[PDB]
Length: 187
Image 1 (cartoon, rainbow, N blue to C red):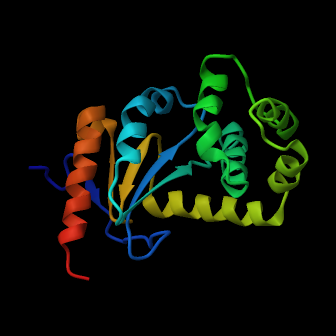
Image 2 (spheres, helix red, strand yellow; image 1 turned 90 degrees about the vertical axis):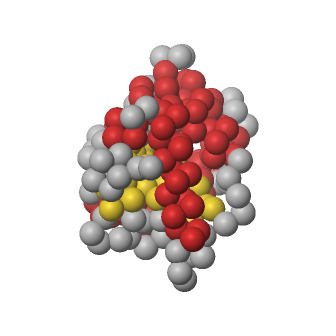
């Protein structure tokens, strides 16, 4: 059994969830984060097997500079509806192929090779709608009081990471435990 204050903490000010009625699981990440890249083989298959009442979401940590730029790329891909399909390839480009993907022109030229419309990528990247999603994501990370990645937050209420949980497998087992806690809770 896990212990509040040890493997996870409870946020004294819970944060609203992106999809009311589902148990939210957020992974805060940065595409350029090696620990984030390394966790992917653990969290990806798990995330695809979650039940119908769970909503898994990735949230880019907008902690400045290149993190903001890569987060803006993430959010642009989500808007275009293609992030899932090019997700692994972005991680691979950054960590294996030496691609910096540090400007929208560079991102668009890379993503074109993965099927992504460059004009639509560029227009979405610079859109007002993306500005709002950026601020939303910033304010969420501030409200979760997250100061590094990868970090998990369940149902806007419980924050934990690989170190606190005690390893990558433990991170998912803890998430499972916390999902069950929320499923059992009175509505």
